[PDB]
Picture (spheres, one colour):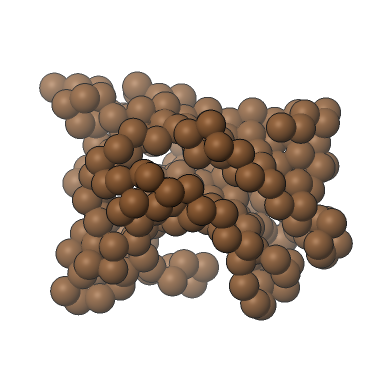
Length: 233
């Protein structure tokens, strides 16, 4: 019997958002005590494993069900988030093991948020499909319109991926398996300066259909670092 993921990994600065009927959020403290369920468990290879059904609960700020970590700079206050200035880096390794009928899940994000804690658009969405990961960077801070697409081909269902998502002074650097692509989001829209951000990682299942089944994503490592210095890449 393996330890729960919040024992194996440092989840002191994450909460877990679930696809149960109530769209429950497990606090960092409860992750640390060893929370585990059908949605979130340690597999035999040790991976922190996220399962979400397409029939799951959905929240006001999410189009689809999720079993997904949400970064908590302050483990007891979701209104504490980071800015466009400085260097903000998430590194992970993982794989997607099962897809919903739509064939598409989101496995990491940077999400915008207002100072008051209210929703703002997603900034980066790491969209996995069998054969390609697309690290979508939103153009407008309004949340209207489309994404800058960044295609990483050759990543199959079951393949190990290594990912880094970095913001350095309003520039997004998106990296899959050593291939780095940049989008100057602040340069494109100064409105991004008026938002704050948080990282996410897990399984945000891009299928809400009755017959869509479920998805499984795994992480083998997950780390976040923040500094108001200027580390480009």
